[PDB]
Amino acid sequence: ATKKAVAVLKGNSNVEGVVTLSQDDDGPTTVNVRITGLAPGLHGFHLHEYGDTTNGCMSTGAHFNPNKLTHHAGDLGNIVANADGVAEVTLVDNQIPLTGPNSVVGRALVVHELGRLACGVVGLTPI
Amino acid sequence: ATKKAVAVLKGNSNVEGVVTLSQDDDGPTTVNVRITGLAPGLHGFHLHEYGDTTNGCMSTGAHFNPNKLTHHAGDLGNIVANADGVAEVTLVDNQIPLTGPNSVVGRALVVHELGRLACGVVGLTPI
Ligand SMILES: [K+]
Ligand SMILES: [K+]
Image 1 (cartoon, each protein chain N blue to C red):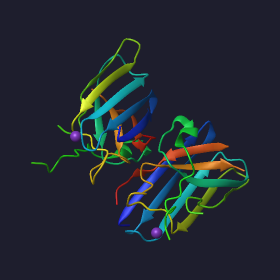
Image 2: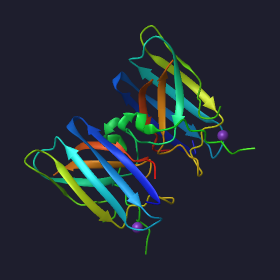
Image 3: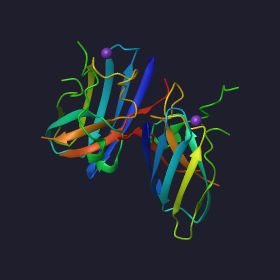
Image 4: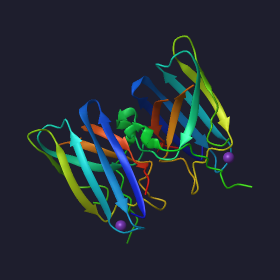
């Protein structure tokens, strides 16, 4: 509500998708995923540090944990592609900030082979 | 220096490119552009409000002026594609913040026909 973002995922394969993110202040973040062109089966799904796709998904750099210094964040959890190669899921994650110094706006989402199949930069979208 | 960003531009044509941005604190922003697949001649080059490419470059929303309330910002200036369809330029703009509430990180860059030929979300990249 209070804030929304989106990432369009593409890569060096036919994998493509869209992920929307919605968070009120610093509350739970609701995440809607639909990705296509995947091989059926389990895939990794992670936040990465940089929203840089100039060298494909390798440029997105390291796995990013927004809550590193706080007293698995960034691993959104494995997703399952169905026999049609489609992964369509809704998640609620309490460690995906859209605000603050470690906000993921301008960083990246990456889908991993269980290696970087597709990725996208997290951008702002109308509230 | 102090901060860097990048956008990869693509659209509903063969236009594609990369723009890097570099700013020390809130000083002048240095902008390196290389875009290809353009028709030779003058093109618009603007900041737009949302880093949303889910419906192509139309989803990037309105022209964005970061300095609207301060006492042409967002128009980066027309660029020229050469006879090879390539626009390769370096600009220094004093109205492209990478920091603050009106930061362009997570927003969009769009190349216009003189209408939205290509666009990309502004993402963070290693300093
Ligand atoms: K939270
Ligand atoms: K400035």
